[PDB]
Image 1 (cartoon, chains in turn brown, red):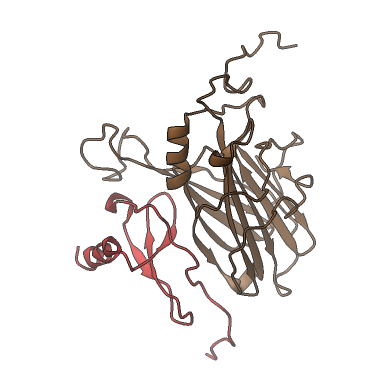
Image 2: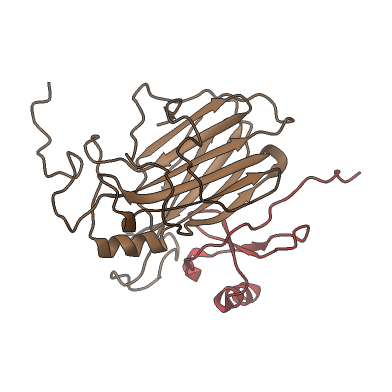
Length: 242
Length: 69
């Protein structure tokens, strides 16, 4: 009975009370349809590999940073991920975008989905908050890349019976902001591919701080279109891959 | 050695807005041609590959630099 009480002001305990502050997070749902050729593969949440640039300037791995001074002028690193599963290998590089703390996945039929997003305050995980200035600044530079490939690792699934932590944000229709960067897809194992992203407050929408983007990939046919990606996938069948 | 039928390929769909300093660019590669909308792709250190519009000078200068050293 942890009576230690997680304080209250903690960004992890609850939302802040500083009007000029918001809990900026991110949500990136994705639905991919397998080709009628690819073999069966339900083994989802096979594994996940988190990586990040040398960041700051602790010890550049053989000239991996500025190679010289590194105060705080400019030095934006990229967080990469390689969530394997569903016979597919999905990877994305978040640059200057909220820190993802929630990773889930699931399989249904000949398609597989993946929920990549940040955690809302009061979930047991950090969820920093900043001012509108830094918010508008981030939502602008924030860019996420993608590069799916055909896997074959028949390894087992590594999940946790612990419910998936949501960002409390909905993929409704709102201001359009080009956040999705490059998107490489090997037809060899991906017929369709829907992209949906969002960035805003995890406590309460703020319109200006709310934005969205996405595309529709079908049989090699792409198409930009801001639509209600709220039902794009069943947020219930999601499973934390740890 | 009969080439495949007509299997689509990787063709830039969108470019990154933020330019990644050379420090995070050890190599690069170009899309293809089967798509009348090519572009230049650059590699990094903690990512993989990311397309880039060749319409921006810095993208060209970056390529010219990798062509030499």
